[PDB]
Amino acid sequence: KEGYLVNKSTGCKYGCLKLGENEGCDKECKAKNQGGSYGYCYAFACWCEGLPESTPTYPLPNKSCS
């Protein structure tokens, strides 16, 4: 699946300024604790594709940031 990376402690998305291709989001999305295949910045927040079912995406069911 895909979606926004969410910080497990705050429940907030990871921000990014450079839109489109973003090595910053790609790196975070690829981290072994996330397990994604590719990442990029979308609407000023890191989007991750190829995430395993086990990896949560924004929003956290019990940790609000909105």
Image (cartoon, rainbow, N blue to C red):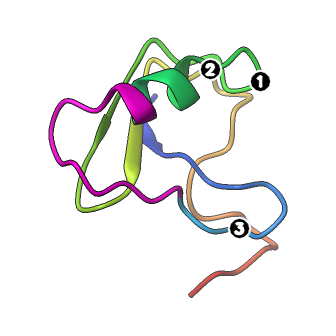
Residue drawn at (17%, 48%) of the image: 19
Question: Which secondary structure lies at badge 1?
Answer: loop
Residue 14 in the image: above or below residue 50: below
Marks 3 and 2: in contact by CB < 8 Å?
Answer: no
Please state which of residues 37 and 60 is positioned toward the viewer in this rendering. 37
Q: Please indicate whether residue 21 sits to the left or right of residue 65 in the image.
A: left
Closer to the camera: disc 2 or disc 1?
1
Image mark count: 3
Question: Which secondary structure lies at badge 2?
Answer: loop
Residue 22 in the image: above or below residue 56: above
Question: Which secondary structure lies at badge 3?
Answer: loop
Q: Position of residue 33 (x, y in %)?
A: 77, 23
Q: Marks 2/3: CA distance?
A: 18 Å
Q: Which residue is mark 3?
A: 11
Farthest-out residue, left = 20
Q: Please indicate whether residue 2 sits to the left or right of residue 9 in the image.
A: left
Sequence-wise, the earlier of marks 2 and 1 is 1
Q: Position of residue 26 (x, y in %)?
A: 41, 24
Q: Read off the magenta span.
A: 14-24
Q: Classify mark 1: residues with Cα within 10 Å, few (<14), some (14-19) or many (20+).
A: few
Q: Which residue is mark 1?
A: 33
Where's the C terminus, which quadrant? Answer: bottom right
Predominant SS along the magenta part: loop
Q: Quadrant of residue 11?
A: bottom right
Q: Which residue is mark 2?
A: 52
